[PDB]
Structure formats: C-alpha cells, structure tokens
Length: 149
Length: 167
Length: 167
Length: 50
Image (cartoon, rainbow over all chains, first blue to last red; front, side, top):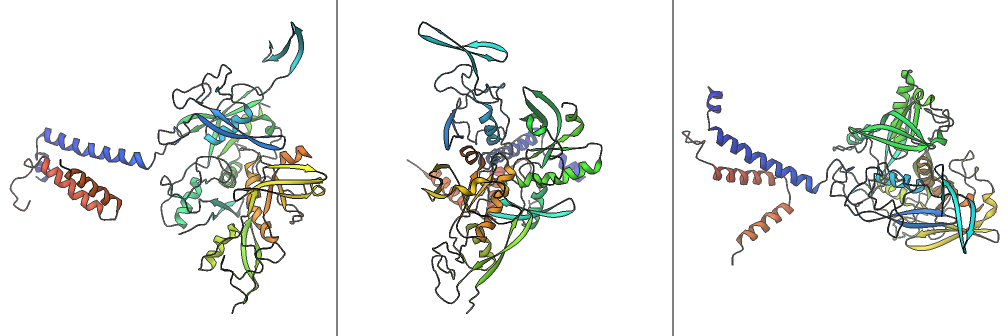
C-alpha cells in the first residue's frame, strides 16, 4: 500500500517536470565544477589550458653558448593530423613559418607529453657545383632523388 | 605549514627496500586537480612532480588525506615498426592508440638494458623481458615503478621475442 | 648552555642513507640572520656552518623553531670559456650573472669525477653528468647535497657535451 | 532606479567567499523554498503535520 500510494502521488507530467528541474540543477552544478577545478583529460588541452599560443620558446646548445629561439603556431585555428602540431604553411619556407627537426621534435614531445612528427632533416651535403652567368649552382641528393639550388 | 621540497618513501625491488624522493612546490599553489603542491606538473623534464599510481595510495596512507594519481606506472607494447633508422613503439593510452619513437642505436646490446642491470640505471625509457618466464615478467613489473619514479615519465615494456626478429 | 659542536643528520643518495655533521660554535653569539650558533658563516673555510636549503627544512623538523637557509645546494652552468690554461664557469646567482674559475688540469679525466665515483670523494667543486639521460641528472641532483655538506661552498653542475667539445 | 537584486547577489557572493561547513544546509533550505514555491499544491493533501 505504501508503494501504491507513492506511485499514484502525482500525474506523469508533474513527475517529468520535477525530474527535469533536478536534472537541470545537477547538470548546472556539474558544469560549475568543471569550469573552476579543471578536467581529468588534460591531454586534449580543452580550453582552460595554454600552449595554444602562437609562439613557443626552446633552447639548444651551440659551440660554447646556450641560445634560445621561437617556434610558431596557428594560435588555435585548425589542426594537422599528419604532423600532430599546429603548423602553418609548413610546406613553404618564409618568415613566420614553422619548421621542426628531430633535434627539437623530441624535446617538444617531452614538453607536451604527446608524440609529434618532424617534417624534414636538419641538413644535407652538397656533392657538385656548377657556375653559370655569375651564379653558382649547388646539387645534392634528397631521399634518393637529385635536387639543386 | 610545510615548506619541504622533497618527500621520502620506500619501495621493494629484488627483495630489498630502496628509497627515492618526490619533489614538491614548497609553498606556492595547491593544484586542486590532485591536491598536491606540484611544480609545473605538465612536463616530463627533470625536477617535475610525478605521482605514480602504485605510490599514490601509500602516500595517501602516510598522509591521512585522499590523493589522486597522475599517470600509470607502465604500459605494455603491442607493435613496432622500423623506418629510416627510427623505431616506433605502439601502446594504448586510456583507450586511444598512440605511439612513441626512439633511436635504434640503443638496441644494439639488450643485456645492459634488460631488467635489473649491474649499473642500476637505465639509458632509455624502455625495458626488455622474456614473456614466457613468469619470474622475469614479475621482476620487470616490480622494478617498473622504481625506475619510473627515479626519472620522470612512464616506462614502456618490450617483449624480447617481438624485437628479436627485427634485428 | 648546550655548546654542541656537531649536529647529526642523514641524507639519501643511491638508495642508501649516509650521515654528515653540521658545525656550531656554542655559547658565543646568536647570528639572528638565521638564528643559529654559527661560526664565521660568511666564509667558506673548513668547519664553517653551511646550512643549505635542502637540509634547512629537515633540520626545522627535528627542532621546533624556524631556521633560515644560507645558500642553495647547487646551480646549473650556462657557458664556459678557456683562456691561458684556465677555465671560467658562468652561472646565475640570485639574478646576477657571475663566474668562477678553475685549473684545466682536473679536466684531463672525467671518469674519476662523474657522479658517484669509487673513491666517494670529489677532487674539485664541479661535477659532470650526461644531460641526455633523465636518470643521470636525477642521480646527480640527489647526490649533490651530500658533497655540498662534506665540503663547504655550492657545487656547480657541468653538462658533458660542452666541456667534451671544448676539450 | 532600484538595485535590491544586486545587493542580494553581493550578499550571496560574500557568503560564498566565507565558506564553512554549514553553507550547504542554507543552500538546501533555499532550494527547498524555491521548489516548494514553484509547484506546491500537487502533493499536499491531508496530514496536517505535513
């Protein structure tokens, strides 16, 4: 009889509305908790974390002095699946472009705690020289194919 | 209340009890994600806070307050592929398939890297064990937490049979 | 009353617990700068009080009064230059760029100076470690404090690459 | 002009700043009052104690 009285307390619509009220308040409280304290999945970087900025600072050792340099990014717009990085026009060389090599890729992966793919090697070796019309031509082999500048 | 930088704890490997330190911020911030005084706990560089799951509960038992771990002690590899002098190690991470790359020069001699070496230190982040021998796997599992607490970032486990045929 | 010349304390290095002494004067002076019975704590002469940051917090718990540290345990080098058989080591000091000099004769052999040697004693104030391995850096950082207390004055850390190249 | 609502919001903000163990019982009373004022009528019958 207690169960019968409980189930017949109110019509179905009132029960639905009362459940909706509590569900909405619970979800609002959960959203408020998620806003301040932070989420467990920090790998996705969500929106509460930085490292979405345009510039990234790194260091490298040359001869006897430690030097610093910047690494550029898109600032948040777009993402590259092939490189797993916020690269901008990485297929062309110009001021403000991004360039990642194995000597810095490992350090950046360690800093971001996620893997990244380098785009090209650091250096190549010239094998022949041709001079024409007051200009000098340099030749080298890249990935088994002949290239020149 | 406390400005201490290091926290002491103990673990058992190869039947003996070793000790290692856990770094702390020392008085700035609280990091409510895992309620511990951490210094830049988002980078695997040296000196960063690293609370493994295996020691998180021991720390939360010595200090009578709940403590949330950050990363698991170790993961098991599943596939390896070589490419232009580099080797990729594939392992799962919270249900997502990921990978990691390292140089092939470290794999020239497995004996100085396997299990508990005489030197007592690891040159790279991976470890090699025999999958058939139960004791070797157990010893590797036991030493995984110690070697992942001595230096930051988790340890990847490699099966000897899998990598034997690639070289 | 208690003119205790030495105070016992312990530290952790290479998984073992060593012991070292800290010197004190006794009934002369109070040194309100760091409230300790120090003996000429402004000079790096032998026997002087060398309360370091890593041990100040520990000593503040055996006793129940606040203690102010004097100098940091160790610093990281930035660049070196050779000249007329002498080597200069540059490092930061509380925001000021300073340098220290030593003879080049000690750098002929690195194996007797790096990390925990067989002798257990360091001939010079500097230490060399391989920076590409996290474990080596962590071991050097842990072992720096013990040698910072066996002998006074801070310990300078050197990366292998630069000194090897200039060698 | 009128600014009573802003004053009440400021009072609630200052109450949230001074957090204690007993803020939850006050929040429960407030939410129960709001819930009872919003629907009422439907589930009140007999039981003068209720």
